[PDB]
Image (cartoon, rainbow over all chains, first blue to last red):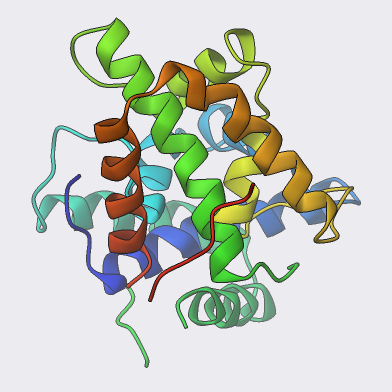
Length: 108
Length: 108
């Protein structure tokens, strides 16, 4: 069981929420755990496996460092930001802190 | 975003860990987020989607109550317990508390 800081869980959670809201905007309702997963891979080449592992701490990963586990999550951010508005962003940030209960730093 | 108590996240996390360790016993290494998922459905008729939602709080569910969200998770427990030993159990219990940092009550 590898250790992942709350700030790491935070950024990882945003990714999931950005891509989610992007789903619930395109579709009318809201995603499915497995659904949203395929949606983040085929549409944004995002690796949900990696992302969920960081959150739940379940499962291991290869590039398990810090500088890496960052440029990777941030890479996803930059990829989604363009398609999300201000509200969507703030909404996911709120939900993240709500899930982690302190302010955290967003990767890049 | 539905609310799920830590005690709910706890039991939900055990399920994932029991089925996981059962995987890393059968296979030599350790699961994959998506892998372990199929493994819990085909081998134990366990609904990982439901379980993960409770943990990460991501995604919604239908039978979102308490008495229900219990007899369901507990149903999974009883299903896995038979195949797990004492160490495996204690190991998952420890990892759970480690992920939630208090002692919690295990469903049935």
